[PDB]
Structure formats: C-alpha cells, structure tokens
C-alpha cells in the first residue's frame, strides 16, 4: 500500500538479483561513485573535442581562480571585459580587480538587507519573506544587472592596484558568517524599533546609520576599502607585450568606459525559462545589491534564437557571459559538459522530466556564471555543436581551466546569456525600449532569482 | 563506566543522530557481553531510514496535492526529501519496525554509507520527477483510486530498485534469525542467534516506550509540549 | 575461419553492444581494474570473518616483513619456530634471524649452480636444462627441504645478533643481478675448460675454488658472514615479559634444537598435485641449494586428509607452513583469500579448468609460502570453513598482517603443507620409512619444482 512492506521489498529484491545487469550494477555501485563508475569513455572519446571554428581573437590570460568564494559572476563579467583591455593595450596578461567589486558588493548587500527588513517590518518574523531575507544576506553570488549596478556607482580598476591579497577574498565563508550574525541582530533591533516608530523617524534614521557604520567597520577589518574613490585619479604603470613601460592616470569610473569599453546601458540578460511565455519580460521581485540600483529583469527567449545570438556575438568577436547549473553533467577532470557523458541508462536510470518542470520541481536552477569564448558550427550546413567555456577555477580545472559544452547541454542545463541590446532583433530589443511590457514578476525565492 | 570503543566515524554523511543514538546503546552490549570493542550497525538503520523517507515523501506530496507547486510547503517537501539527518523519535520509529543488529553482519562497506551525496542526488532527482507525475494524476483522480494506488507502488518499487544498487537490503528481516559469533575480552568465542527486533531489547536493552526528548526552546513557554 | 575477420568481429561487437549487461561492463571495465570494479562487498561482508575456534596459543609477535625479496619461505619456516622460543622464554616479541639463513642460502645456491653446470657440461648450451640453470641461479625462493638443508649445516640464531640491516636483505634485486651476471661468465669458463679436461682434473678443481672464492668475496660486500660459525658459541642477553634480563650462551646448531625445538628429522612436506596418484612420492629432479643436501620430495595426498592433518596439527598447538598461488584470489587490502570474492560471473567470465589441468597448462603453481595459525570448524558437526594466515609483508598488509583463507581456496589454490612424520597415518608415514617407494621424478622446470 502506501507504507513500505517488508515482504514486498524482499520479494522485489529477489527479482532484481536474478537480473544479471542488476547484479553487476550493485557490485560496482557499492565500490565507486556513480559518476566515476558510469563515466563513458567511448562517448568521452568523441565529445572531448577542442577544435572551435568560431573563437574570440584575444586569449583569456591568465586563467583566473575565485578560490573559496561565490564570485564567479564577477570573474565571468570581468573576464568578458579584460579581453578589451588586453587587446587595446597590447598586454600579455591582464586582470581587472574582482576584489574591488567584491568589497562594494558585500558592503551594499549588508546595507540593502537593512532596507529590506525595514520595508517588510509589517510581516511576521516567521513569514516566508522575512525568513528568506534572513537566510543569506551577504552571499557572494549575484546577477549581471547587479554587476552593472556596481560598475555604474564604482567603475572598474586594474587588479594591480587592489587584488586577492586578503584571506577573505579567497575564503569568504567566515567573514560572511560574522557579518550575517550581526545583521540578524540588527534585523531584530530594527523591527523592534519599528513597532513603536516610523521609518522616517529621526531615531530610526540614526539607528540605521550606526548599523551601516558597524557594517563598514567590520568589513574594513577583513578587506581594505579600495585605494581610490570612483571619481578619484589613480596612476597605473605597466609593461606591454613589447617590454615597453607605460603609465595611465584615470579614475575607476573613467577607466571602465575608456579602457574596459563598458557602456552599462547596452547589456541585457536573456533567459530561457520554459515555464513562461517567450517574448515576455521576467522580473525578480526585491533581488538586488545596491539600494536604489536597477532591478533584475530578463527577456524570456527560445533556445533557437539564443543559440544564434551567441554565434553572432562570437562572430562579432565578443565573449558571452552565461549562467547554468554547475556541476550538473560536468566532468571537472576533463572539462566536458555533456548530459550523456555517463552511462546511467545502462543501469536503467532515466530522467524524462522537462526543463520547465525541473525548474518548477526544485531540481534545476542557475548556480554558476561562466564565459563562452568560442563555438563550433557543424562544418557543412547544420548548426552549433559545442561551445568553448572559460571557467574561473584555476588552470588545473578542466583542460587548463577551459571547458567544452554541448549544444544539448546549452539547451537543457543553461538558463541565461548576456548580450548588448543592439544585437537583438527589433522585435526583441523593443521589449526593453517600449512601455507596454509589464514584466511577469516572480518572488525573490524563485529559482531564476537564485543568483550565481 | 563503560568506554566508547571504538571511536566511530560517520564520514561524508549526516548520520550523526544514528551514530549517537546507537553509541548510547552500544555501551549496554559492550558491558553485558564483556567485549573490548563493539558497534551496532548504523548502516542498517541508514538503509531503512532512506527507503522510508523516499516513501514518506510520496505520501507528503499526495496529501499536499491541493496546494500550488510554488507554495512554501510543496517547495519545502521538494528541497531535501532524502537527507541523512534525523531526530530521536525518527530513530525509534525505525527501531520499532526494524530492530537493531551488530555491525559485524552489515557495516559501512558500501561507498554510499561514507559518501552519500551522489546517492541522495540520484534519488532526489527521481523523486522530483515522481512528485510531478503524482500531482498530475491527482488532478484528474482521487488518491484512493486504483490507478493512483498502482502508480505509487511502481514508484516505491523503482525507489527500492535504485537503493539496492548502492546498498544491499539487510541480510535478515526484522523477525528473522541471525547467528553472530564473537570473542569476549577473555579471548573466548561465543555465538548468539537472535532476530533484529529481539536483539534490540534483549541485548541492546532498548524499550522504545521510555525515551522522550526534552528541548530548550526559549521562544515558547516551558512545561509545554512542542510538536 | 582461423584468421580474424574484420566483418565478423564488427558483427559480434554489434551483437554484444545490444546486451545491457555488456554495455555496463565495458563502461566500468574501461575505468577501473577488474578486481577493484568486481570486488563483491555482499560476499566480503560474510567472508571477512576473524573468529577462529582453533588457534595456536602463542601470538606471532612481531609481524615480519620480507620487503623486496623472495624470502617468504624462510620467514614462514622461522615464523613457525619463533613461537617455540617466544613461549619457552616468555618473551613479548621475538624473531629468529631470517638474514642468517638468507646469506647461507644464496652462497650455497651460487656454489650449487657451478656443480649443476659441471654435471650438465655434456649438454648443448641451448638445451632446456642448461638454459634453465642459467635463468635464475641465485633466486631468493626455496622449499622446506631446502630450509632444513640449511638448518642442518648452519643451525639457527636470534635476529638480535644478525638482522635485516644490510640494504640487500630488503632489496635483493641488484645483488642477485650482479652475482648472476658473474655466474653466467663462470658457467662459460667452466664448460670451456670441461671440453678439454675432466672434472676430477686438478686444473678444474683449482678453477672451481677460485670461482667459489670470488662468489664469497662478492657476497661479503653486500652482507657480512654471520658473526659466529655453526659450532661456535654466542652470548645473547634479552629481557623477558617480566622486564627480567637473561643471558644465553649457545651455538647456532645447539640453539636450533635446544631453544627453537627443531628436530630436522621430523618434518615432511605433503603436496596436493592432482596430476599424479595420491599415496605416491613425488621428487623434483636437481632442485636444491646445499650441494649434497637433501632432495625435495613430497608425499602426494588428497585434500580431505590434508584438511584433517591441518586441524589436528593446529589442535596440537603448532602452526602450519603452507605454499600456494599468491596473489590469486587474494585481496591484500582486507586480507581475504576467497575464489568467489570478485563478481566475474556478472560479466560472464567463468573458469571450468580443473586443478590438475591448471598446473599442466601453465596457469597455477606455488609462488608464496605463508603460515596457518588457526582455523574454524563449522560449529555443529561439519568441517573447516576458513583458516587464519600469517603473512610476512608487514603489519599493514591484510588485517594487521593477517589473512583469512577459505577451505575452498585451500583446496584449489594451495598446493603444500608441512607436517611432522609422526602426525601422519601409519599408511602415509611408511611411504617415507619404507623402501618400495620409488618417487615419481619430475624435471627441475616442473611447476611443483618452482620454489616459493
Ligand atoms: Hg558562483
Ligand atoms: Hg559556431
Ligand atoms: Hg555557435
Ligand atoms: Hg543558455
Ligand atoms: Hg617467496
Ligand atoms: Hg578447525
Ligand atoms: Hg580446520
Ligand atoms: Hg594446501
């Protein structure tokens, strides 16, 4: 019936043990990890292909490593931009400061959290929203819109002026824990004061300032505030590929446009969320980092268009920031991302659940942001077969830091790319520049609202 | 008085509760049988606990079929249906239905007892597929329906099929006899024939009817029962 | 036909790939070692049993390690005897000198080889015998009769006076290589001189003495000749379990009888060679170490009697030297010796070839000598199920140096035990003390003539 019957399971066992495939399966599966045991080398032999006919001219030098932090999104976003500096300044190796953005992102989220608590002060402490706000207020992960929020207010700077030196940039767990413990204390203090008074109250205003101050005080103990303010000048001496020395005096905000070539007004993030109609705008309620910054909004598009937008973008010599479900169907040793790389059907394990339902049923979401730097169209008259992916896990992960993702993987376990609005078809670009477009608003706890 | 021998290791699993609950009981066997080292089978309970939670989940989905897929409860049920962790009452639930057995007859040999992440992931991925399938069938039919009943049995079967690939069902059924040969501290050999359920009372000295768990939750008044 | 047809093998492939068990098998077998992949934990769960109702009272202390040498036979033979000293002198730990015997064994084999070449000087250099003599003249392995040959001429000594200090005792490969290279030079020189002269010739006699001398000269460079001669007195101070100091003055030859309790006249080696009739004596032609020592002769007996002789011997509190085919069906990590421990039938691999044919067809022979220190008779009214085995590979091999061997393994992959003649049934003992018994003579290259 609905309960586990002991006779029933022992009878099923008896039946399974009579099948030779099951006998072999239990023997091997009790010995090794399923992924290790089932890795299919016949398939690997064909899929581990590193020839890409369409690639970004500039090489990702050097391979970056986020270490023990969830700063992939910042690495990937800056990895896309570093290529412009590398190229425009004829540099052998170059990196924009990921830590720079990380410092400001964490400060802003702690501050942003306080406001979120204030705006939901009318809800019970045990409500879904309040408990959600309290879950991970300072997590490292983020979205592209959140990336632009920071670049708009703070600009970009070369890693040479501010790098991953502090312990907390490469091992952020403890720092976040200390901060979050305080914020949860502040959350209580704010709400309590909000029972008697209004937010506009002089007392509340004073209270929030003292919280902001302690938040900055604590963050400055683990990382130094960047050396220059956004509009403040910095001098950067460097050597080009020709062993020639140069000096650049700029400001974080000027450097971002002038050298990094970012016009914050052009990138838009396209998502592939099968639970909603395409051509529709999807907005994640409350998701953000900079209080007052822009909101996360995606244009929902089909995989056919998405695939093309990626090829065109690559052909226009630009890398493509994308978000997917790591490490689903990802072999870190080889760097292969193929949903058929492991022989699960040999053990009769099959998964018919569709993408939309996978998202709906708590099974798949975006968890990591990486960079597409190449692709390979079937050399004849067909379409893209695989893509070249640059990860931020050091040069030993995958094949010298690089991965290869199948088209099928792209369709199934990848949910987002970032393009410039001018690359979109008029029909799509308009959804961003029109007004009729009322976005489908999803809660903060929706799987597409789960950062990277 | 009795010493915890040997020190146990749950490895990469959240089976602490089973280790701790059995660590409390092992002391009785160790003592009553004059043994230098002794361990009750944690894996025994682990196998049944995981099977039962997968099954239990299905029922939870059926009983909340009227709620939206994105409701707080349904999303919660879908979060970690087979997690290793548990409570003491859940520990007794298992001992009542399955009894206890010496680790010598069924130990941490399988890869999945000491590295359960993958196993749980494979199971949970299936259960989330089943969750959808059940709810869909529940839109048109009632749970008492012959069709639904059949559906749940085929899910239960696949769940057991998949679990048996990573761990073997214990060697004896709860009321089935087993023979256990051992050596006491005096280098003397002994043989015990018992059943998992008898061994639990007789040797492990557990009367499931006596333990109660006291909690210290300052948000609620004391002397009050919390469920 | 008799040749490999390409169409045929691709057609068979096509057929095998349609079977689900084959698909899973190729997937896993391309990833792991067959023994690792097929190790059956369901079976291991039952077979890894360390309860033995019949065990030798004294404990093997400490666990020995032959390291990189084939001195198992000496370790096992002395491991059987150490128990007497340990017991009779109330010692916590004790070891007889394995190196002592090793030095003399190697010296004697080099010398013995020379004689073998002289006695086969009439045969062509490329004959089977001469090429065999030239293959491994100084190999570390040996037989029990060869063990007694040494004890009779040299006695036994405590390891405290002469141990495994030299590099060559634990890494004998190079030493053997240097010696063997010289001996092969000597072999040529002898044969050449034997074409013109007779062995009794003064010149030949002189020649062999100069070879013997160079052989000793070279061996003394890698190991020191033992400190005392066989009839020479030595003084050994030791501490018993009671922290009490003692001193023993003895001679290597006296110590062997007096303390080690060995009467070289009692042990006989029983073999289980299914290719020959039981009750028959089997002699290995030319096999030896000490020129003039005894010859290797085995009494061929059935497994039923053999099993009993082992139980009785164990009950008489004595350990049993045995020889088998290591590492066939041996799991070094657990220490389990079980021919059904790996699930080969799950991949359809089955071996019907019988023991006698296995020996005949170059598949099974004795390769390692170990020690049975216990057994477990089915506690009811049946027979032995398993045996407790002491190996000489250190305390980390198996379970703290110890192994457990099934009865079935004993019957199939074990070919010899050593008992005292007085333990045999009159019918069997007589074969040794009669005269009618003309032994079945096997060549030196016969698999039973392959040492340990
Ligand atoms: Hg991340
Ligand atoms: Hg392409
Ligand atoms: Hg492409
Ligand atoms: Hg995508
Ligand atoms: Hg050997
Ligand atoms: Hg026995
Ligand atoms: Hg026995
Ligand atoms: Hg044998």
Image (tube, coloured by chain):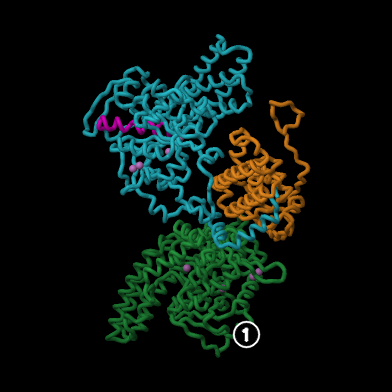
Chain colours: A cyan, B orange, C green
C88 lies above or below C422: above
Residue displayed at 48% across by 75% down: C146
Question: Image quadrant of ligand 3?
Answer: top left
Where is residue B102? Give x, y as percent. 68, 53
Can you identify the residue that label 1 sits on? Answer: C427
Q: Is residue B54 left or right of residue A250?
A: right
Residue at the farthest top position: A202
Location of residue C48 in the rendering, given as x and y in whole percent from the top left corner: 60, 60
Q: Indicate the quadrant containing the N terminus of chain B: top left, top right, bottom left or bottom right.
A: top right
Would residue C49 be seen by someone viewing this image from the given angle? no
The image shows residue B131 at horizontal and vertical percentages of 60, 43
Which structural element holds mark 1?
helix
Q: Determine the chain carrying the residue at label 1.
A: C
Asked where in the image residue A122 lies, by quadrant, the reply is top right
Which residue range is magenta in the image? Answer: A72-90
Seen at 39% across and 22% down, the residue is: A152
Is A77 inside the magenta-drawn segment? yes
Question: In the rendered view of the protein, which quadrant contains the C terminus of chain B?
Answer: top right
Count every numbered label the image shows and give the total: 1
Residue C5: say if magenta: no
The residue positioned 46% from the left and 52% from the top of the image is A39
């Amino acid at each position: 019936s609905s309960s586990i019957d002991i006779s029933k399971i022992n009878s099923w066992n008896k039946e399974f043990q009579s099948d030779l495939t099951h006998q072999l399966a239990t023997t091997v599966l009790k010995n090794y990890n399923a992924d290790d045991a089932l890795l299919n080398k016949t398939r690997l032999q064909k899929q581990d292909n590193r020839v890409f006919n369409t690639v970004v001219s500039t090489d990702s030098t050097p391979v970056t490593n986020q270490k023990s932090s969830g700063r992939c999104w910042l690495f990937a976003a800056t990895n896309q931009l570093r290529l412009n500096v590398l190229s425009e300044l004829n540099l052998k190796e170059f990196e924009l400061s990921q830590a720079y953005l990380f410092f400001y992102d964490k400060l802003e989220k702690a501050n942003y959290f306080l406001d979120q608590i204030v705006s939901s002060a009318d809800q019970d402490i045990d409500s879904r929203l309040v408990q959600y706000l309290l879950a991970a207020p300072t997590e490292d992960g983020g979205q592209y819109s959140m990336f632009l929020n920071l670049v708009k207010k703070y600009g970009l700077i070369p890693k040479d002026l501010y790098g991953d030196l502090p312990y907390s940039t490469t091992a952020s767990r403890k720092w976040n824990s200390l901060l979050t413990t305080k914020l949860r204390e502040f959350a209580e203090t704010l709400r309590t004061a909000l029972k008697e008074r209004s937010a506009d109250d002089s007392i509340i205003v004073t209270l929030r300032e003292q919280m902001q101050r302690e938040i900055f005080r604590l963050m400055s103990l683990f990382m130094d505030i960047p050396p220059v303010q956004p509009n403040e000048q910095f001098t950067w001496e460097y050597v080009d590929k020709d062993k020639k020395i140069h000096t650049i005096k700029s400001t974080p905000l000027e450097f971002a446009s002038k050298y990094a070539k970012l016009d914050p007004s052009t990138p838009v993030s396209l998502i592939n969320d099968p639970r909603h109609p395409y051509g529709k705008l999807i907005k994640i309620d409350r998701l953000g980092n900079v209080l007052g910054g822009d909101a996360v909004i995606y244009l929902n598009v089909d995989n056919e268009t998405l695939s093309k937008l990626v090829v065109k973008r690559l052909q226009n010599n630009k890398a493509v920031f994308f978000g997917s479900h790591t490490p689903k169907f990802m072999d870190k040793k080889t760097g292969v991302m193929d949903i058929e790389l492991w022989n699960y059907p040999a053990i009769g394990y099959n998964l018919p659940q569709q993408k939309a339902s996978r998202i709906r049923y708590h099974e798949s979401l975006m968890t990591h942001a990486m960079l597409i730097t190449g692709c390979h169209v079937d050399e004849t008259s067909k379409l893209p077969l695989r893509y070249r992916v640059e990860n931020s896990w050091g040069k030993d992960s995958g094949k010298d830091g690089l991965y290869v993702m199948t088209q099928k993987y792209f369709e199934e376990y990848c949910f987002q790319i970032v393009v410039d609005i001018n690359e979109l078809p008029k029909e799509l670009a308009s959804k961003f520049t029109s007004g009729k477009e009322e976005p489908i608003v999803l809660p903060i706890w929706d799987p597409m609202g789960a950062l990277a």
